Length: 30
Length: 30
Length: 30
Ligand code: NA
Ligand code: NA
Ligand code: NA
Image 1 (spheres, rainbow over the protein chains, first blue to last red):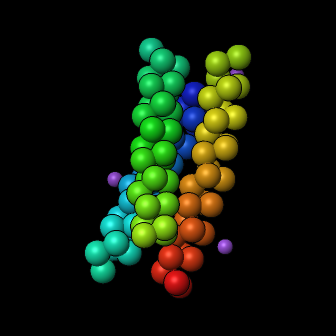
Image 2 (image 1 turned 135 degrees about the horizontal axis):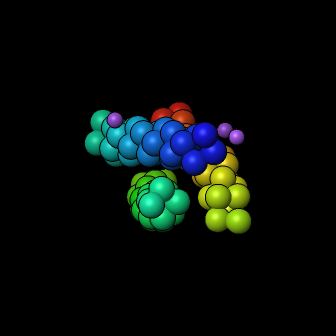
């Protein structure tokens, strides 16, 4: 499961990056 | 295969992280 | 070697995203 674990971590990091972008947009415009 | 796909995803995530940093910095300095 | 390098990059990106979360919280507070 070594590659599968890295794939799951990358998917989580991609979700966290999207959430940070949404938080920055809220700060910029809100 | 799987390792090539993970390498490509990591490269894209690093590019989008740099883009987020630049936007955040621009907001902070502005 | 490539798997080890990708694991190291993903671990670093976790810390980078946490630091960006802290910067966004500071912008919220400022
Ligand atoms: Na085994
Ligand atoms: Na999603
Ligand atoms: Na902090």
